[PDB]
Amino acid sequence: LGISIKVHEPPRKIERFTLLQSVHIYKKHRVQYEMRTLYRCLELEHLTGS
Amino acid sequence: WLIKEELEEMLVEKLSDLDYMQFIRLLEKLLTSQCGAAEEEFVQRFRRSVKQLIEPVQYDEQGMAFSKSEGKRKTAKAEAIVYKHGSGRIKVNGIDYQLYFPITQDREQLMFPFHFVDRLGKHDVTCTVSGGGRSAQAGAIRLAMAKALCSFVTEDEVEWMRQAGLLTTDPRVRERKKPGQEGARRKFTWKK
Amino acid sequence: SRYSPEFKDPLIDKEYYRKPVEELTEEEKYVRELKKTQLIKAAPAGKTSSVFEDPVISKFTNMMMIGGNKVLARSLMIQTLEAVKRKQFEKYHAASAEEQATIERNPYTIFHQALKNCEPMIGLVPIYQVPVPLPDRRRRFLAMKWMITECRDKKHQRTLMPEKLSHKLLEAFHNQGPVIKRKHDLHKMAEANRALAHY
Amino acid sequence: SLSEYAFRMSRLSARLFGEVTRPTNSKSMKVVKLFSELPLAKKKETYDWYP
Amino acid sequence: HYVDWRMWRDVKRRKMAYEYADERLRINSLRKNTILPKILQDVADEEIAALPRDSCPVRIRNRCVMTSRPRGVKRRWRLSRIVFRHLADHGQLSGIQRATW
Amino acid sequence: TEADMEEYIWENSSSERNILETLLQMKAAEKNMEINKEELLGTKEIEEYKKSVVSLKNEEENENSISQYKESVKRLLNVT
Amino acid sequence: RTNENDPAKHGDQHEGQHYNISPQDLETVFPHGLPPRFVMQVKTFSEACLMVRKPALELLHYLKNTSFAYPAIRYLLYGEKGTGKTLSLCHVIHFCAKQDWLILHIPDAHLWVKNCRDLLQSSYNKQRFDQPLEASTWLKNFKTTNERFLNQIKVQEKYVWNKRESTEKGSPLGEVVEQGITRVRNATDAVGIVLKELKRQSSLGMFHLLVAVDGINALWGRTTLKREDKSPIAPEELALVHNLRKMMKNDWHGGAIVSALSQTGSLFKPRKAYLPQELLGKEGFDALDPFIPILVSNYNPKEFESCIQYYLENNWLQHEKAPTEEGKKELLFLSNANPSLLERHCAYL
Ligand SMILES: Nc1ncnc2c1ncn2[C@@H]1O[C@H](COP(=O)(O)OP(=O)(O)OP(=O)(O)O)[C@@H](O)[C@H]1O
Ligand SMILES: Nc1nc2c(ncn2[C@@H]2O[C@H](COP(=O)(O)OP(=O)(O)O)[C@@H](O)[C@H]2O)c(=O)[nH]1
């Protein structure tokens, strides 16, 4: 489409939390879960509204 | 000699440890028997192979000849620029080193690379360091300065610095805390 | 450890790399050639190539360190050395020439000599508290730990660590003081338990 | 307290931006913070917690 | 047909709090200031006390939306730790994965 | 007020009053009452001193600016 | 070494050479103000060899070329931390004292604005405060330094200490100084009186006053002192600080004022800050304007070599490898030719 575009990668984010592994009582033992949000930034420049 | 896994991959079969040892001993006997090239290539079929790259010198607007490198230590990253000719001046983040590093240990760490190759006062250094603490920044600047100075010392001095540890990046970083224990290794007080 | 076993400890010694090739023996040449193919650990932040680097004083400073406060321990050590040197200079200037010749003014020499004098030749371990010989590393560690513990004693009130450590080091340099007494008491106990030492 | 010029200028800026133009302690700014935000019970997470 | 009578009580509390949210907000705003006369603040206090007990938003409890567990509920997913672990372990939850670093 | 003025004005400031008083005392001590207020404030030396003081107060401070201020003060105070 | 005590000999050609303060001069001219590290160095070496540096030479030349008729010119030594501003000021003080000037030396203005638990309300002025201990110590030191002129100077006004005690006009200034020293409770007031007297005597041409204040930025900075109601105290609320502020004004002739900035011991100032404006504050710079700033920097190669040789000749560098060129380069790098860092580093070798 003839649009000036650059690309970069912002640093990823990793959100981690921890939950009790067992059901009743095993506080010493946990499971750690994480969510990874990876980013990609496309910077388009000098393009009209349409 | 290739490991048992490599031999199994080469022969697409499964071999025991004793079979591998027998084959290795036979190959060693072949090598020690003054084998010719026809057998030396056969040996090299089963042979597996076991230096630091140096940045080139650059030139600036002022006309000085310089090299630039970078290093890291813990959570600190530093970039150093060492000029071929200077007077021992080191400026960190635009600040003189004796002011940015009041601790004598950090200044000694900065001195260590130039002192090792006997080049105190023979260069000028500009460093930009970010992250970590005073000692991590000092170590990162030391590593970056050594890597940049490799471009001006002889190859023998480069090897000597590598043997002195001035060029190896310290992989020792903070170990993550694990659940169920106080720290990275400190377990909770074991009750009875 | 984050270092693989392939890594080797660095050898920070300029004289080692300044040795001429001809003086190198066959074994030394082989070692130098092998070192070119070995991974080398990064130089620790403690030791450098400085001509003033004393491993004994560095180890003593590390032992004096409390809670990773290396700056404070180094400050205490340098203050102790300065106090020792100042006391020696005062004694030298206050003494006659005949005594001036004998008076020692190097703080490093005094520190090393005091540590050597405080080294216990033989100690004791349960097997009965059997007297047993001590390796040189254990001897040096015991001397340093005894000096530090004696200086940290609550018997001294309001006196700073550098002054106390300088006083104890000067006492040990003349084979006197509580630490030398502790070493002599340990040796006396070993002599007493010589009978049980056959276990 | 403050220079009268700076005080009047800050009051003019607050009037332009719609902020409180009269002196007010935090206890009464609690009214402003109450009416600026939605009530906790009115948030979609609260009244529509369970399906 | 909620999971338990506790979830039913919480649903009733949430509905009643949403119904009385604006009246509570207005009366509390009358109370939480140092400008209006103290007598008006006292009558506002008795007015807000006259409101039904279950209309107070503090009584709202964030229970798990599938097992009515009162504790161990992640606010983002509104699920108890056990149910969240089950769904994440089966992989039915997008993005969530076992954390290893 | 002084605090309300982010831009430093050299006029009616402590600098002008102090330099005028210093010059007046200097010439009174010299016994040669040859100076005048406008005559002093119009000279090039006073202009350079004002420029250096404005550069220090308003723009930035560094070794070059301090050296320039020192040179201007030395020229004004007749001591070098 | 250039073991010389004559203050009229050393000059630009003596840059890097040594200047000796005799023990009598050390005891009389300097009962205070000398940096504690150099006090220890003097007590150990049994010598008082100050290296002659360019800033000190420039200040000496300015003071030699000045005229007492002119209003008191303000000179301000400044530089990075531990560059030798205090010792340059001390060198100037000693030279002026040998020139038979009257030395009005403040050892440290930071002491008067911090760590004072004996603060009292001023009887002479209920809006101010008095520091009896600091004032008494400074009065003792001032009497020690300027004893020869202490009896000669005549007071110009009658001053009252209590309903029963007063000092008559025309009495020696020694009477007021000894009254302040002995009667500690009035000492602060006496200090101000002395300053006041000195100022007018300087205008009268009785002598050549040299006001020497170290850490001048403490006058217009901030004070950590607190009121009985746990309230902060402005610097001008201290009688000593207000009197020193009055003394700093250039509305008097008959000498010159010399001050030295010192971030060390300052309150509410960043460590790396050394420039005159940053250390002084806007009010301080306005009060001191106009002034001649003199930059004190690290040693040059010649000065560093001279200092190292002076330490070696005194055998201070007891380490075996110190005399070697490698040790000299190591010391130069680890100190960056900074006099304080170099001395502290060499103190444990
Ligand atoms: N001219 C000199 N000759 C010898 N030693 C000097 C000289 N100038 C400074 N020093 C050294 O500097 C140290 C003291 O520094 P000094 O107090 O003079 O400097 P400063 O920057 O004014 O200090 P501070 O910021 O602590 O007030 C001493 O160890 C002293 O030996
Ligand atoms: N006790 C006492 N102190 C005096 C007397 N005269 C002067 N002083 C001291 O000298 C200072 C006088 O300063 P002054 O010239 O009055 O300055 P001013 O207060 O701003 O007008 C005060 O701080 C007093 O402590 C006196 O007669 N008795």
Image (cartoon, coloured by chain):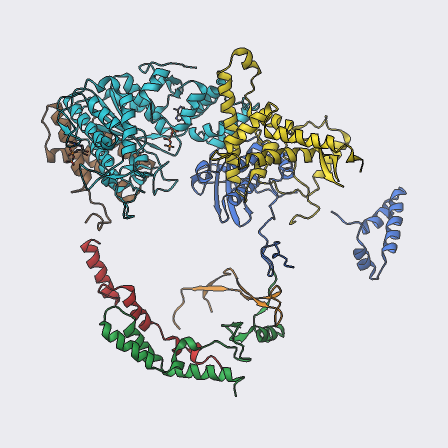
Chain colours: A orange, B blue, C yellow, D red, E green, F brown, G cyan
Q: Position of residue A32 (x, y in %)?
A: 59, 65
Q: Which residue ends up furthest to the bottom in the rendered image?
A: E1
Q: Residue at x 24, y 62 (%)?
A: D13
Q: Nearer the viewer, residue C180 or G304?
A: C180
Q: Residue at x 29, y 66 (%)?
A: D27
Say if residue C184 shows up in the picture. yes
Of G107 and C156, which appears nearest the observer? C156
Q: Quadrant of ligand 2?
A: top left
Residue B87: x, y in percent? 48, 31
**Residue G11 visible at all:** no
**Left or right: where does residue D22 sit relative to residue B144?**
left
Q: Quadrant of the C terminus of chain C?
A: top right
**Residue F24's image quarter?**
top left
Residue G180: which quarter of the image? top left
Q: Position of residue C89 (x, y in %)?
A: 50, 20
Horizontal arrangement in the rendering, residue F70 relative to residue C196 (left or right): left
Query: Which x, y percent locates residue F33?
Result: 9, 27
Task: Looking at the picture, tell me which residue is in the foreground, G300 or G136.
Answer: G136
Residue in front for this viewpoint, A42 or E19 = E19
Question: Splitting the image into 4 quarters, where does residue C141 fall?
Answer: top right
Q: Residue drawn at (55%, 47%), measured in percent from left and top?
A: B72
Q: In the picture provided, is G312 more to the left or to the right than C115?
A: left
Judged left or right of residue G207, residue B162 is right
